[PDB]
Image 1 (cartoon, one colour):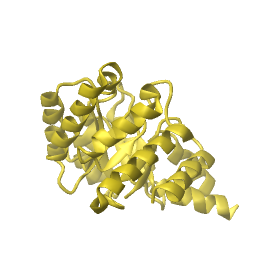
Image 2 (cartoon, rainbow, N blue to C red):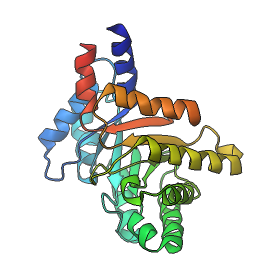
Image 3 (cartoon, rainbow, N blue to C red):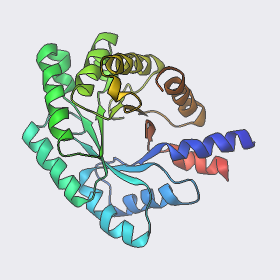
Length: 250
């Protein structure tokens, strides 16, 4: 089944291979990084908590030289409720430790509870973080499974894009509802509106679909949505997908 193997190969190249079990150890991170480069197609990134960024940048880069997948670090994660000061301090430390990309949760609870103030706060936090991230990718997690409504998903997406987010990320994977085709469609609607109003940002904005993506067919579905309606510029976030896809290729 070469068609499936070809799709599987392409999808690994777009996947952020993820480990976000808070009680995890260097052993878990070593296994994650080895998996990301096991055989030929390498994952786009490894995605971890800030506490493990140094280990990857130092230890893993010493064991695997060169180590190609980018180091993506989550931030303000999963709850989105840290002060701007803490988020910025944590981000500076993560960058110091070797982080290449930042997957940042905004305060979606405040957007739900007190929308206008929450949207302004999300814009401001995203922008402040972006100032630390020249020529680095900032992905902003909007938590679509909590926002829920078309109106909040679109408004939140617009708010963070106006804060100069590079990517919109659907979900933390830490709440019950993750990406669905509908909420991805709403994000795409919002990005298109942002681009229309900011033409210089065309082909500069990415989408990362994360949470509950564990099979090739579903990964392909979302890629196709981005390709048809939206278009580096697309990622999958999964803790399991790469392992599955390597088996498909073998």
